[PDB]
Structure formats: structure tokens, C-alpha cells
Amino acid sequence: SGKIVRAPSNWTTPHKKMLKEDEDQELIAFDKLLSWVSETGVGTEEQAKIVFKKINAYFYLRCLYPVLPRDPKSMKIFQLNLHFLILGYIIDDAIEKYNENEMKELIAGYNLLQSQVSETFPNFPSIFEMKQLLGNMKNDFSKSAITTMFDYVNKTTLILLEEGEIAEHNVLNYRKRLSNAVAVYFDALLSKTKSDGAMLWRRCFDALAIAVYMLTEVFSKTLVKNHTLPVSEFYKFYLLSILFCVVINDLHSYERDKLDDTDSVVKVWFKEGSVANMEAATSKVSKILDAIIQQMYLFVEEGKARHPELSEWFERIAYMTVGWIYIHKTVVPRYVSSPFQIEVVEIHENMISNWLLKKDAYGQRVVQQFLKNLNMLY
Ligand SMILES: [Cl-]
């Protein structure tokens, strides 16, 4: 085939087991999501139910975290982020239609509240109190968008503070980086209202993916372990993994992206004339995805050698990366129906070295040019 993506067999084992599980209704806590709908002013009960089914939201998040720790902190942050996946989707559906001035107004409201809210640590204001703080806004939905973002960041902070296991300065650093991710998400939307590489880099932030990647730090206890991995290296892993998501998503969304002005690497190839058909486009996508998995494997193995105390974190990033395959091929209805898909070939342990040696020039060039972006989220 020309559509093959190679991946280590043991990078897919957790997902295969997870997809046989029943939905965990107690963990989903749908009634608690409905309470948050009412409190935030985002969505309705009916809309929350429709979005949950459209995303297949529980299995969507479990594809990213097929191994999920059961300590209370991890369970609480998983549940909060499952609920925020729903509200964030509804917020995104609304504000991606904002024009430039509406996005600037939204960003200004978010930035006005940032210090006065964060400086109340650990006694954060409720959504009601925060809505009173905001100045008049021309678009009324913006107040609900802003205070939902803050309530999510505040609730995250309070979960991490529970029982004092994580030192406060690390809780606050995580909070700041999560708020940074929200700010860069808004900025990415603003940019779209006004090169190929800058377009691709923008695609890494236009869906707040960093927020779900940061959960790996909670689940694998990197906020409590003393380690020598600088924060910049965390984001190397995050952004390489996000690139995988962007590229496979562009393949599965092309039939829709064809018809609107959404950015897509497949659309760029057709516009520049570098692919003549979807067979060629799928081949190019497979070479990129395949190269990312090779580069991720090398980063994971080098990370484990240098920082053995973070071995679990490195592995979980690998699983999260493979999770995007299952999200697009198995879990999300609108992605599963794409006639344009890649095919996974599993690499067994005996063949790992020979797999890594066999590289593709095109896929490697895309990955190497992308990683040059790394040389504000943190
Ligand atoms: Cl501003």
C-alpha cells in the first residue's frame, strides 16, 4: 500500500483493551455536566447531549489516555476535562464565527480578568462574580466564553491543590501555562479573521490541544517528582504529537474542508499542484504520520535514557499520539466515515531497530522543518 503508517505494536495495546470497555457512567457524571451548563450559560441540556454523541466524548478522551490512573486527583481532572471538552466545543462553534473586532473584544475581556482573578488564589471567584467583573461587551456570549475558561482554569487549580501533595509554586506554574494555552487559542482564532509553515503552526493552537496534553503531567505525577526535564522539552513532545493530530485530521476532514475556508495541508497540496488526487494526498499524509511516529519513538527512548524517572510520562505521550489514530478511525462518527484513511502496520519488538532505520525522505523533511518552529506557551 501507499497509505501505511508503521507503529510499535505495544503502542497500540492499551487502546485495543480500552475500546472493549463499557462507558463509565459514574466517571462521566453527566448530571454534573448539566449543572455546569446551567451555571456557565454555555449550551443547553439537549445541546450537551448532542455534542457528547458527536464527539463520542468519553471514548475520545480515553483514546488519549487509554491507561487512566484511578487516584482522586486524576479522576477529578479527567472528569473536569471531559466536561470542558463539551463546553469548549460549544464555545468554539460560536467564537470561530466571530469577526476580527469581536475576537479582539473577547481577548480584551479575557486579559482584563486575568490578574484580578489569578491573584485571588486560592479563593477564586465564582462564574457569577466573574461575570460582574467584566466590562460591557457588545457580544453577550463573550462573557460566558470568558468566565467558562476561567472557571475551568480555576477548577483545575483547586483540584491540583487538594491535600497539598503538589507544591504550590508548581500548581501555579501549571495554572499559568494552562491560561497561556487559552490565550494562544484565542490569538489563533484572531489570526484567522485577518505562509504554509505559519499556517501549519497556527493549526497546532486553534483547538486548545495543549490543555489536554498538560493532563499527562497530572496523570504521570511530573508535578511532584523531582526531575531534570525542562519545561521546553515537554512542549517539544506536545507539539510533535499535535502535528500528528493536525495531519490525520486534515485527511479525515478534507471532504468538509473542501467546501469552506478552513485551513488544511491537503488543500495546500491541491492548490500548489503537488498532488493530483486523493490517492496521492493520502500517500503524502501517511509518510508524514509515519515519520512522526519514528521521531516520537526516538524522542521517547532518548528521554527515558536521560530521565528514567519520567518513563511513564514518555510512554503516555506515545499512547496519546497513537490515540489520534483511534479517534479518527474508530471513535468519532464524522471522522470514521472518511473514505480517505491510513492503515496501521504494527512493528514487533524484534523489528524495532530495522523499522526505525527505514525512513522516508519526504516525511522526514516535513518533521524536521516543523521542529525548527521550536527554536508564548511557557
Ligand atoms: Cl487586550
Image (cartoon, rainbow, N blue to C red):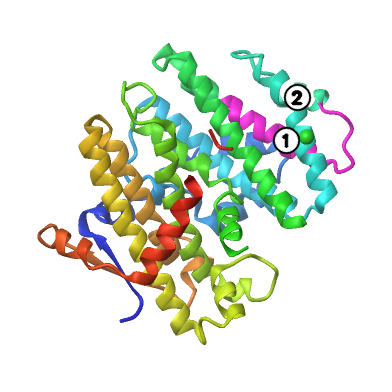
Q: Residue at x 52, y 38 (%)?
A: 81
Q: Where does the image place residue 149, in percent across and percent down from the top left? A: 65, 35
Q: Where does the image place residue 269, in percent across and percent down from the top left? A: 55, 76
Q: Is residue 79 above or below residue 116?
A: below
Residue assigned mark 2: 130
Q: In the figure, residue 260 lies in which quadrant?
A: bottom right
Residue assigned mark 1: 146
Report if residue 17 is visible in the image: no
The amino acid marked with disc number 2 is: Met
Q: In the figure, residue 326 lies in which quadrant?
A: bottom left
CA distance for labels 2 and 1: 9 Å
Residue lying furthest bottom: 276
User: Badges 2 and 1: C-beta atoms under 8 Å apart?
Assistant: yes
Q: Residue at x 29, y 58 (%)?
A: 294
- SS for dot 2: helix
Report if residue 335 is visible in the image: yes
Q: Residue at x 39, y 61 (%)?
A: 325
Range of the magenta residues? 134-155
Quadrant in which the N terminus is drawn? bottom left
Mark closest to the chain's N terminus, 2 or 1: 2
In this rendering, would 191 be left or right of 54?
Answer: right
